[PDB]
Amino acid sequence: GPSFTIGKAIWLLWGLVFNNSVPVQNPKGTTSKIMVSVWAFFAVIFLA
Amino acid sequence: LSSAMWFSWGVLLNSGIGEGAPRSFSARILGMVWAGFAMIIVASYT
Image (cartoon, rainbow over all chains, first blue to last red; front, side, top):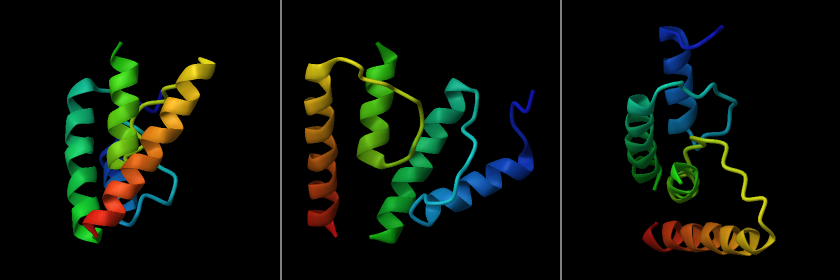
């Protein structure tokens, strides 16, 4: 049902940036996984 | 399999992508060691 939404991607990215504490919903696409991983790397570098 | 690669990448980058479950008893120790190594690397970089 709830595959993905524009409003949920923002929440997931915001949670990832701030140490990835708040619960989020993962995407259902292989292509989006690479973008999520790159964003996570950027977030970890930024936090450090 | 892709599940192991996804789990390793998520552990290293702390992204939560994927739900890899290493039910193998031997693989559990390797997973814990990999998580510790990733934590040590991040702490050293910081």
